[PDB]
Length: 49
Length: 48
Image (cartoon, rainbow over all chains, first blue to last red; front, side):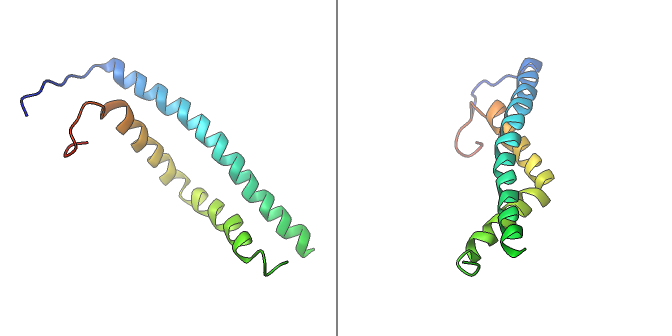
């Protein structure tokens, strides 16, 4: 396309920052939701017993 | 209620089991997402 593009190690570092940050965010959030999947397991268990 | 919560217990089990047994595949998904974010800003629709 004859359009200029570049790259730097700074962007790799920033990419690692994004990986760490959004991973702890989504890990914790979606695993509180999966904790709630386990709360569903608790509901099933208490109902059955 | 136990048959009324058929879909409910199914979601409660299978959603966790899917995000869990694929949790390393979901780690991969996080990697794909953050790569596509950080690097693939300046690109046209064929390459994006």
